[PDB]
Length: 280
Ligand SMILES: COc1ccc(Cl)cc1-c1nn(C)cc1NC(=O)c1cncc2cn[nH]c12
Image (tube, rainbow, N blue to C red):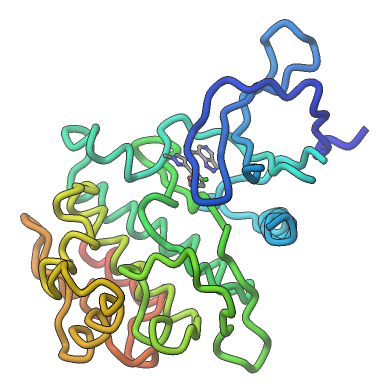
């Protein structure tokens, strides 16, 4: 028997966890004994794109890191089986736990995301969807990168992957090169980290979201010119403001993620040293 092969007949749905445009994550119990004693697992499936989910499954199967959600297996069409993290994402957790989470804990979460991202980077992968909604909460002390739906492999001796299909893109988290030429470098993930760091520092407050803040800067009435206006503001050197109660030294580390040219951005290794210096 293969412990990574899950039988559909024993995979019992409890409740929905969340959904995207094409994919959904559900809480299930894998109950072969039929008595509700089986382990609870997170299950990713496509709504009634199979090729992309199969590639996501193979990517996650070969990632092994404390700050990366654990692959458990598959249910053959296919479903992706992972460990279940009941606290859900930072987007859902932080607004409900401001009393539990202080700056020091926010900076440790920041270091944790950089380590998981730095490991993905070392495996020649670009995430392309690094946002707080994709960071899962293991406990009040630990976070994990929780989804790899847009992840792509960067070729050896090549510095980026060029994306053909940009239809479901989080443009308010995207670096200028991604917006202008659909070019995804590891430095593009560093740009997205800075935006995810802004979210985490504002406790994922809806009124202060990256989307809300940028629309206040560029104007909300440009329709189809919105990405063009976004690129214009970025070219002008304009950036997301300092989160309230965020010290300048943390803001300055965030500003280095957003250097217009990919080459001038601080790397994940560099950011880790930065946060650890502030924690000590
Ligand atoms: C990263 O999260 C998502 C990614 C894609 C989709 Cl389609 C939904 C969610 C989602 N939305 N929300 C609101 C919560 C989600 N997920 C969880 O709570 C969850 C818990 N334990 C383990 C895993 C693995 N993937 N997701 C997990």
